[PDB]
Image (tube, rainbow, N blue to C red; front, side, top):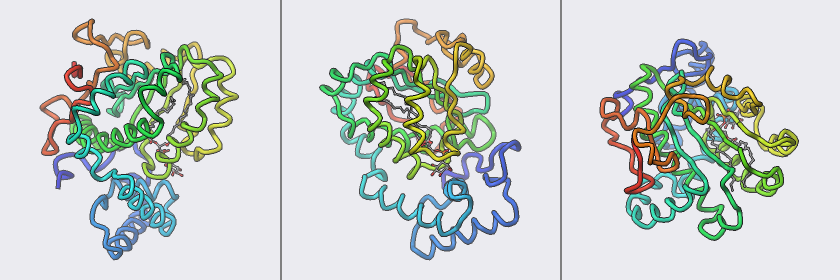
Amino acid sequence: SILDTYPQICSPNALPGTPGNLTKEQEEALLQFRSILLEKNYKERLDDSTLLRFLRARKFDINASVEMFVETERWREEYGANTIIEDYENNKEAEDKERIKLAKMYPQYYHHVDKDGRPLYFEELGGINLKKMYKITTEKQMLRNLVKEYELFATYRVPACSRRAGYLIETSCTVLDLKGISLSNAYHVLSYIKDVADISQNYYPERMGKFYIIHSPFGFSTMFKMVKPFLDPVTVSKIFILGSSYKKELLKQIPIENLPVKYGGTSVLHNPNDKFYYSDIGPWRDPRYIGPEGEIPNIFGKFTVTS
Ligand SMILES: CCCCCCCC/C=C\CCCCCCCC(=O)O[C@H](COC(=O)CCCCCCCCCCCCCCCCC)COP(=O)(O)O[C@@H]1[C@H](O)[C@H](O)[C@@H](O)[C@H](O)[C@H]1O
């Protein structure tokens, strides 16, 4: 399989329960877990990395893990997640046209990696005008975009970043920029945030590495109290709402040369004219780290900036 073309064991610093560092009990739990799924006639997504993510999410409770994995497969099938990339490719022209319009309003882009080799992801929310946004897209569509990215992450970003890092990468480093949002709108989209949380928590376990929230308005901490109800404790412990010293905290986790200038780093697009909201820069663009999976498609069509 493709798995033989990139590291399947995490770095030596990874906590037990991860690929390459299991206790005897865990390693035994994993074999039993796979056996049960194999008996249920499951074929795909049964590799160590995937299975350990579900096991970790359920603290290695085999039956709870089986139940979680079964429901995930169910959803993947009904949601169309197993063919989300293919279907997008067959509709690229139309979908790209609408995505281009949404990107400028709601920047979503990866820009290199963090110090551990994790794909570095950025989102900027301050330019969103809900009214204008609801005229060009729907929450439904934004969720499907999210799901598609989850698939692109596992398909293209992980193999490449793992080959570069020298070890298996299973998570991302996210920076949520809230500069310019109204605490009021934060409350207003609680519903969508819940939907995002449901899909991620339930179908994409152990995919969060580091998650920073910067430039949040005063009072945000209170609004966040309403988000925590639908986030597992493990997830909440990965979320960090930074203050005025955010650049210094980001510099502790991300190479200065990989962090955009406005966030405290020195990274600049090769062509200062290009926009980060049409960019997709990282190891998965480096021919040296792209494998049999091929190169990731261009989500922003012709405007896609890969440098
Ligand atoms: C309409 C625009 C709204 C965009 C507002 C959208 C904001 C969302 C922003 C970005 C999208 C998030 C992408 C997340 C990338 C990380 C990968 C990922 O999916 O991680 C997953 C995390 O799932 C999530 O919860 C994702 C949702 C994150 C919510 C972040 C809080 C949002 C902050 C709100 C800001 C306010 C918005 C301002 C509004 C202004 C707009 C005018 C898996 O977690 P992990 O710890 O890896 O494993 C879990 C496992 O899974 C559980 O089962 C187990 O029980 C548990 O023990 C663990 O094993």
